[PDB]
Amino acid sequence: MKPIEIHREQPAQHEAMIQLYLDPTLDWFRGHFPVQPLLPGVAQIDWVMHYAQTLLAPGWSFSSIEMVKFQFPLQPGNTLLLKINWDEKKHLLTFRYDLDQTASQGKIKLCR
Amino acid sequence: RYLPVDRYLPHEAPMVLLEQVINVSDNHVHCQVTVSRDGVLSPFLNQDGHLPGWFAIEMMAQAIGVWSGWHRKERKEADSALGMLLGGRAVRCQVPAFTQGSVLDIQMNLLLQDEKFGSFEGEISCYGTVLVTGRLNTYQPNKTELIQLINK
Ligand code: NA
Protein backbone atom coordinates (compact mmCIF):
# COMPACT_ATOMS: atom_id res chain seq x y z
CA MET A 1 0.00 0.00 0.00
CA LYS A 2 2.92 2.45 0.59
CA PRO A 3 4.82 3.78 -2.46
CA ILE A 4 8.61 3.83 -2.95
CA GLU A 5 10.23 6.66 -0.98
CA ILE A 6 13.14 8.23 -2.88
CA HIS A 7 13.89 11.09 -0.44
CA ARG A 8 12.48 12.99 2.55
CA GLU A 9 13.25 16.42 3.97
CA GLN A 10 11.89 18.28 6.96
CA PRO A 11 13.00 21.97 6.80
CA ALA A 12 10.85 22.80 9.86
CA GLN A 13 9.40 20.49 12.55
CA HIS A 14 5.89 21.20 11.10
CA GLU A 15 6.73 20.68 7.38
CA ALA A 16 7.73 17.74 5.20
CA MET A 17 8.73 17.25 1.58
CA ILE A 18 8.70 13.67 0.29
CA GLN A 19 9.71 12.41 -3.15
CA LEU A 20 7.68 9.31 -4.09
CA TYR A 21 7.78 6.90 -7.01
CA LEU A 22 4.73 5.02 -8.31
CA ASP A 23 5.65 1.43 -9.24
CA PRO A 24 3.41 -0.57 -11.66
CA THR A 25 3.05 -3.33 -9.01
CA LEU A 26 1.67 -0.95 -6.34
CA ASP A 27 -1.56 -2.67 -5.24
CA TRP A 28 -3.72 0.51 -5.53
CA PHE A 29 -3.49 0.12 -9.33
CA ARG A 30 -4.87 -3.48 -9.26
CA GLY A 31 -8.30 -3.35 -10.93
CA HIS A 32 -8.08 0.46 -11.02
CA PHE A 33 -8.35 0.29 -13.97
CA PRO A 34 -8.02 -2.47 -16.63
CA VAL A 35 -7.78 0.10 -19.52
CA GLN A 36 -5.50 2.51 -17.56
CA PRO A 37 -3.80 2.21 -14.16
CA LEU A 38 -4.67 5.40 -12.24
CA LEU A 39 -3.76 6.25 -8.66
CA PRO A 40 -6.99 6.60 -6.61
CA GLY A 41 -7.66 9.95 -4.88
CA VAL A 42 -8.00 8.10 -1.56
CA ALA A 43 -4.44 6.69 -1.85
CA GLN A 44 -3.09 10.25 -2.05
CA ILE A 45 -5.02 11.09 1.15
CA ASP A 46 -3.83 7.81 2.74
CA TRP A 47 -0.12 8.74 2.37
CA VAL A 48 -0.68 12.32 3.57
CA MET A 49 -2.15 10.79 6.74
CA HIS A 50 0.79 8.32 7.10
CA TYR A 51 3.46 11.02 6.92
CA ALA A 52 1.33 13.40 9.02
CA GLN A 53 0.72 10.90 11.84
CA THR A 54 4.40 9.67 11.78
CA LEU A 55 6.39 12.91 11.20
CA LEU A 56 4.19 15.96 11.96
CA ALA A 57 1.26 15.28 14.29
CA PRO A 58 1.83 12.05 16.28
CA GLY A 59 -1.22 11.09 18.38
CA TRP A 60 -3.61 13.15 16.20
CA SER A 61 -6.47 11.44 14.38
CA PHE A 62 -8.44 12.10 11.22
CA SER A 63 -11.48 14.41 11.45
CA SER A 64 -12.37 15.80 8.00
CA ILE A 65 -11.31 16.60 4.46
CA GLU A 66 -12.40 20.23 4.27
CA MET A 67 -11.37 20.56 0.63
CA VAL A 68 -9.50 18.33 -1.81
CA LYS A 69 -8.90 18.84 -5.54
CA PHE A 70 -7.50 16.20 -7.87
CA GLN A 71 -6.53 18.18 -10.96
CA PHE A 72 -4.22 15.81 -12.92
CA PRO A 73 -4.28 11.99 -13.29
CA LEU A 74 -1.38 10.00 -11.82
CA GLN A 75 -0.14 6.69 -13.23
CA PRO A 76 2.72 4.22 -12.73
CA GLY A 77 6.16 5.61 -13.59
CA ASN A 78 5.32 9.06 -12.19
CA THR A 79 7.51 10.66 -9.55
CA LEU A 80 5.63 12.84 -7.07
CA LEU A 81 6.76 15.61 -4.74
CA LEU A 82 4.49 15.68 -1.67
CA LYS A 83 4.53 18.85 0.46
CA ILE A 84 2.69 18.75 3.82
CA ASN A 85 2.25 21.52 6.41
CA TRP A 86 0.78 20.92 9.89
CA ASP A 87 -0.70 23.95 11.69
CA GLU A 88 -1.34 22.67 15.21
CA LYS A 89 -3.15 25.79 16.44
CA LYS A 90 -5.56 25.60 13.44
CA HIS A 91 -5.91 21.75 13.70
CA LEU A 92 -5.08 22.00 9.98
CA LEU A 93 -3.03 19.77 7.71
CA THR A 94 -2.45 21.12 4.19
CA PHE A 95 -0.90 19.19 1.30
CA ARG A 96 0.03 19.41 -2.33
CA TYR A 97 1.25 16.73 -4.75
CA ASP A 98 3.35 18.04 -7.63
CA LEU A 99 4.52 16.05 -10.64
CA ASP A 100 8.33 15.97 -10.40
CA GLN A 101 2.53 20.34 -12.49
CA THR A 102 0.20 20.28 -9.42
CA ALA A 103 -1.64 16.95 -9.34
CA SER A 104 -3.64 17.47 -6.16
CA GLN A 105 -4.04 19.71 -3.14
CA GLY A 106 -6.14 19.76 0.00
CA LYS A 107 -6.98 20.69 3.57
CA ILE A 108 -7.58 18.06 6.29
CA LYS A 109 -8.68 18.66 9.89
CA LEU A 110 -7.24 16.47 12.65
CA CYS A 111 -8.51 15.95 16.21
CA ARG A 112 -6.77 14.66 19.34
CA ARG B 1 -32.76 -7.13 -7.60
CA TYR B 2 -29.39 -5.75 -8.63
CA LEU B 3 -26.27 -7.25 -10.18
CA PRO B 4 -23.20 -7.73 -7.94
CA VAL B 5 -21.95 -4.21 -7.15
CA ASP B 6 -18.66 -4.71 -9.12
CA ARG B 7 -20.73 -5.18 -12.34
CA TYR B 8 -21.77 -1.48 -12.23
CA LEU B 9 -18.15 -0.18 -11.87
CA PRO B 10 -15.08 -0.05 -14.13
CA HIS B 11 -13.27 -1.02 -10.87
CA GLU B 12 -12.30 -4.63 -10.22
CA ALA B 13 -11.18 -6.50 -7.08
CA PRO B 14 -9.25 -5.67 -4.98
CA MET B 15 -10.33 -2.01 -5.66
CA VAL B 16 -14.10 -2.46 -5.24
CA LEU B 17 -14.85 -1.18 -1.75
CA LEU B 18 -18.62 -1.91 -1.66
CA GLU B 19 -20.46 -5.23 -1.22
CA GLN B 20 -24.19 -4.65 -1.90
CA VAL B 21 -26.43 -2.38 -4.02
CA ILE B 22 -29.50 -1.66 -1.84
CA ASN B 23 -31.34 0.90 -4.00
CA VAL B 24 -30.89 3.08 -7.07
CA SER B 25 -33.13 5.74 -8.60
CA ASP B 26 -32.82 8.74 -10.93
CA ASN B 27 -31.52 11.00 -8.09
CA HIS B 28 -30.31 8.57 -5.36
CA VAL B 29 -28.09 5.56 -4.65
CA HIS B 30 -27.83 3.38 -1.53
CA CYS B 31 -25.01 0.83 -1.20
CA GLN B 32 -23.74 -1.21 1.70
CA VAL B 33 -20.45 -2.61 2.97
CA THR B 34 -19.27 -4.29 6.18
CA VAL B 35 -15.96 -3.58 7.95
CA SER B 36 -14.62 -7.15 8.11
CA ARG B 37 -11.36 -9.11 7.92
CA ASP B 38 -12.83 -11.41 5.21
CA GLY B 39 -14.47 -8.77 2.96
CA VAL B 40 -13.53 -6.18 0.35
CA LEU B 41 -12.29 -3.67 2.97
CA SER B 42 -9.76 -6.09 4.59
CA PRO B 43 -6.71 -4.78 2.61
CA PHE B 44 -7.44 -1.23 3.91
CA LEU B 45 -7.77 -1.90 7.67
CA ASN B 46 -5.24 -0.28 10.02
CA GLN B 47 -3.12 -2.18 12.60
CA ASP B 48 -6.02 -2.17 15.10
CA GLY B 49 -8.48 -3.81 12.63
CA HIS B 50 -10.37 -0.58 11.75
CA LEU B 51 -11.04 1.20 8.44
CA PRO B 52 -9.62 4.73 8.55
CA GLY B 53 -12.23 7.51 8.24
CA TRP B 54 -10.72 8.97 5.07
CA PHE B 55 -11.83 5.88 3.09
CA ALA B 56 -15.33 7.44 3.33
CA ILE B 57 -14.51 9.45 0.19
CA GLU B 58 -13.72 6.27 -1.79
CA MET B 59 -16.83 4.44 -0.58
CA MET B 60 -18.92 7.55 -1.49
CA ALA B 61 -17.14 7.88 -4.85
CA GLN B 62 -17.86 4.25 -5.70
CA ALA B 63 -21.52 4.66 -4.73
CA ILE B 64 -21.70 7.46 -7.32
CA GLY B 65 -20.00 5.02 -9.72
CA VAL B 66 -22.73 2.44 -9.05
CA TRP B 67 -25.39 5.12 -9.76
CA SER B 68 -23.92 5.96 -13.18
CA GLY B 69 -23.26 2.28 -13.97
CA TRP B 70 -26.87 1.26 -13.24
CA HIS B 71 -28.26 4.04 -15.46
CA ARG B 72 -25.90 3.16 -18.34
CA LYS B 73 -27.08 -0.49 -18.10
CA GLU B 74 -30.77 0.54 -18.03
CA ARG B 75 -30.13 2.77 -21.09
CA LYS B 76 -28.22 -0.03 -22.94
CA GLU B 77 -25.15 2.26 -23.10
CA ALA B 78 -21.54 1.00 -23.20
CA ASP B 79 -19.98 0.27 -19.79
CA SER B 80 -17.70 3.02 -18.44
CA ALA B 81 -14.03 1.91 -18.39
CA LEU B 82 -12.74 4.76 -16.19
CA GLY B 83 -13.86 6.79 -13.19
CA MET B 84 -12.22 9.77 -11.54
CA LEU B 85 -12.77 11.66 -8.35
CA LEU B 86 -12.18 15.39 -9.08
CA GLY B 87 -12.87 16.74 -5.61
CA GLY B 88 -14.49 16.62 -2.19
CA ARG B 89 -15.85 19.30 0.12
CA ALA B 90 -16.50 19.14 3.87
CA VAL B 91 -16.19 15.37 4.11
CA ARG B 92 -16.61 15.36 7.90
CA CYS B 93 -16.37 12.18 9.98
CA GLN B 94 -17.72 11.75 13.52
CA VAL B 95 -15.07 9.05 14.17
CA PRO B 96 -11.40 8.65 13.15
CA ALA B 97 -11.98 5.06 11.95
CA PHE B 98 -14.85 2.66 11.28
CA THR B 99 -14.75 -0.19 13.77
CA GLN B 100 -14.48 -3.85 12.77
CA GLY B 101 -17.99 -5.35 12.41
CA SER B 102 -19.69 -2.07 11.38
CA VAL B 103 -22.32 -2.37 8.64
CA LEU B 104 -21.96 0.86 6.64
CA ASP B 105 -24.78 2.43 4.58
CA ILE B 106 -23.49 4.73 1.84
CA GLN B 107 -26.30 7.00 0.56
CA MET B 108 -25.61 9.58 -2.20
CA ASN B 109 -28.05 12.25 -3.52
CA LEU B 110 -27.67 13.73 -7.01
CA LEU B 111 -27.01 17.50 -7.17
CA LEU B 112 -25.89 17.95 -10.83
CA GLN B 113 -24.95 15.54 -13.66
CA ASP B 114 -24.15 15.52 -17.41
CA GLU B 115 -22.48 13.12 -19.94
CA LYS B 116 -19.25 12.93 -17.88
CA PHE B 117 -19.32 15.23 -14.78
CA GLY B 118 -21.30 14.43 -11.61
CA SER B 119 -21.89 16.33 -8.37
CA PHE B 120 -23.35 14.50 -5.34
CA GLU B 121 -24.03 15.10 -1.64
CA GLY B 122 -23.46 12.07 0.59
CA GLU B 123 -23.95 10.35 3.92
CA ILE B 124 -22.37 7.29 5.56
CA SER B 125 -24.49 5.88 8.39
CA CYS B 126 -24.45 2.80 10.63
CA TYR B 127 -27.89 1.59 11.83
CA GLY B 128 -29.31 5.08 11.19
CA THR B 129 -26.53 6.97 13.02
CA VAL B 130 -24.89 9.43 10.62
CA LEU B 131 -21.08 9.06 10.73
CA VAL B 132 -19.97 11.02 7.62
CA THR B 133 -21.47 13.84 5.52
CA GLY B 134 -19.92 15.35 2.39
CA ARG B 135 -20.07 16.55 -1.22
CA LEU B 136 -18.14 14.85 -4.04
CA ASN B 137 -17.41 15.77 -7.67
CA THR B 138 -16.66 13.02 -10.22
CA TYR B 139 -15.59 12.68 -13.86
CA GLN B 140 -15.99 9.74 -16.24
CA PRO B 141 -13.67 10.29 -19.22
CA ASN B 142 -13.11 8.22 -22.35
CA LYS B 143 -9.70 6.55 -22.61
CA THR B 144 -8.83 8.96 -25.49
CA GLU B 145 -9.93 11.97 -23.43
CA LEU B 146 -7.61 10.75 -20.66
CA ILE B 147 -4.67 10.40 -23.12
CA GLN B 148 -5.30 13.98 -24.33
CA LEU B 149 -5.44 15.13 -20.68
CA ILE B 150 -2.17 13.32 -19.84
CA ASN B 151 -0.40 14.71 -22.95
CA LYS B 152 -1.88 18.18 -23.70
NA1 NA C 1 -16.19 -3.96 -12.39
Image (tube, coloured by chain):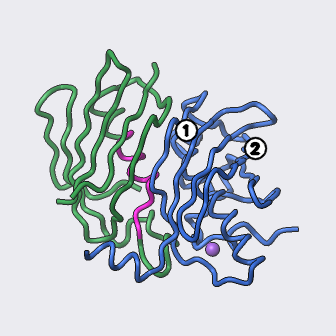
Chain colours: A green, B blue
Residue at left offset 65%, top offset 36% = B99
Q: Is residue A70 above or below residue A57?
A: below
Q: Position of residue B71 (x, y in %)?
A: 73, 71
Image-based side of B29 in relation to B44, left or right: right
Q: Marks 1 and 2, how far apart in space?
A: 14 Å
Residue at left offset 31%, top offset 19% = A88
Query: Do marks 1 and 2 share a subunit?
Result: yes
Asked if ligand 1 lies within 8 A of label 1, the reply is: no
Residue at left offset 18%, top offset 42% = A17
Would you say residue A74 sits in the magenta stretch? Answer: no
Q: Is residue B67 above or below residue A18?
A: below
Q: Position of residue B8 (x, y in %)?
A: 69, 71
**Disc number at residue B103?**
2
Residue at left offset 78%, top offset 76% = B74
Q: Are marks 1 and 2 in contact (CB under 8 Å)?
A: no
Which residue is the extreme one toward the left? A11
The mark nearer the N terminus, 1 or 2, is: 1
Image-based side of A35 in relation to B56, left or right: left
> The disc labelled 2 sits on which kind of residue?
Val
Which residue is the extreme one toward the top? A89
The chain identifier of the residue carrying mark 1 reads B
> The disc labelled 1 sits on which kind of residue?
Gly
Disc 1: which residue: B53
Magenta-colored span: A38-49
Image-based side of B92 in relation to A55, left or right: right
| Secondary structure category for the residue under label 1 | helix
Q: Quadrant of the N terminus of chain B?
A: bottom right
| Secondary structure category for the residue under label 2 | strand
Image-based side of B80 in relation to A72, left or right: right
Residue A51's quadrant in the figure? top left
Q: Is residue B118 above or below residue B125?
A: below
